[PDB]
Amino acid sequence: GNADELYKEXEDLQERXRKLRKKXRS
Amino acid sequence: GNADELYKEXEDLQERXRKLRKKXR
Amino acid sequence: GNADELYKEXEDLQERXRKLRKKXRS
Amino acid sequence: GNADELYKEXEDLQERXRKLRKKXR
Ligand code: NA
Ligand code: NA
Image 1 (cartoon, each protein chain N blue to C red):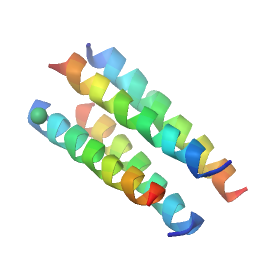
Image 2: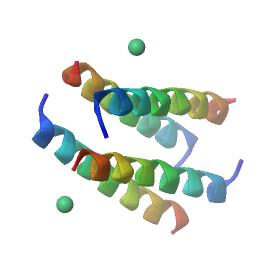
Image 3: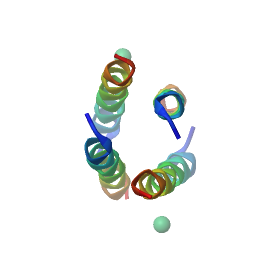
Image 4: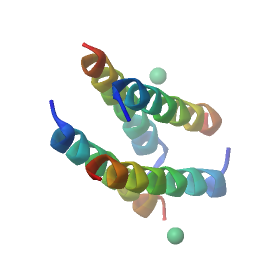
């Protein structure tokens, strides 16, 4: 648990959500 | 209770996470 | 931006997701 | 591409957030 882990997880989750939103509409 | 509602929900959650990242930095 | 805000947001989002999962199945 | 898949996805995202909170504390 550190700033780099928090940042990486937050950015991975945001990208996972962009992909999920994209496929949901398609 | 449709795809549009889930889509808006997902965008809202994504932007709440971006706001945490921006505040953290 | 601080530890209390991060904690509160993470806990609010988890609870919002418990409610969304609950209503999705129902 | 059904409700079961979205349900598992949502549980996965929720548990990933609990893991960040636990690591933070
Ligand atoms: Na970046
Ligand atoms: Na608590």
